Length: 422
Image 1: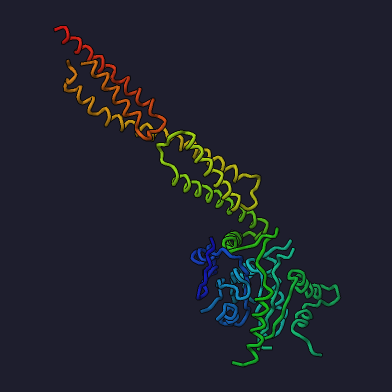
Image 2: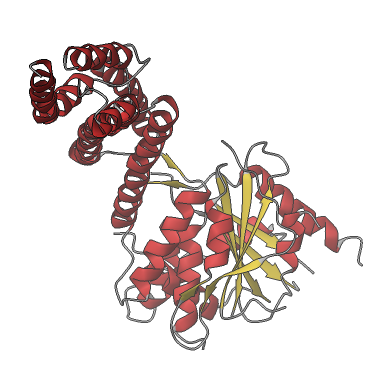
């Protein structure tokens, strides 16, 4: 089951309106339904607003300030891959650093979109967002630093030269090297672009898109764990609830929370499959108990397989043992329902087979006599035993009914013997 989604316009994902970080639930239902692997490239534009121009070129064809906006499009070069675009723009206060580090945590490519040239303020700002996403192999996202509006030096050498530290040890050169060295090791792969309709300006914006479409990889987690639309939803809920609660987002707790949710979903898909198979193949008045248990075993082994194909790092087999106890409870319930259905069905058979019989004795039709009453009851037991499928509780309910009619049979014998003497 694969559901490919293509949306025409971007939506709001995280809201920083007022003071609390609110999550747009409608954007999560669209994201969760995505089954393909996602390539999340986050676009963060500082200072001047860029009318989300880079986001539209990456999508294949309004203000995104205090919050993150998401846009899911199919990858143009990678088949069966979903391109997820995150756009956000913003001395800037501390509330925008939280959403920038969020976009950095959710992304596999971080597009830093500033203006003019690389100043100390933009480096200090990028250094600040890397601290909220704690860093304590290749799951770190790559940096794409774009510069708008402007000894031959290439843009790549400029970015590598804008981060080259100067030797020294005073508390004003160390503070000059600390942010420029903290992002040197944070982003292992770096790329720089210089921007300036003009026929030459689109040349740099297309090779920027060609670099994003050819280099940006599927987002992964520590442990070689590919991320799709469902797992990115849990990453957002884990990271947002971490920031909104005052905690620093730890990544080892995000993967455990994701594992505990995919396992809870696994035991539900197993029970759902078991309920479907059991509800479609079982009519309660079964012929024999063994035929009901064989139906349960076939549905049980299929449910266990559905769990194993959807589980993810089952800790101590706690979810598998939980599933096996629920299946055993359904085995005891269906066997109890099988006996009740056999008793209730067989009770309705006696009301119709012995209905006219106990109604005939009420009018004294055997008050002759009794030898014709025992042979008529015996005749009705042959019709009851030759019913097509009545369950396994057929013998116990018949005897329980016959022992309740002993007083009626003894009374007919008294009347039959009372008139033979006269």
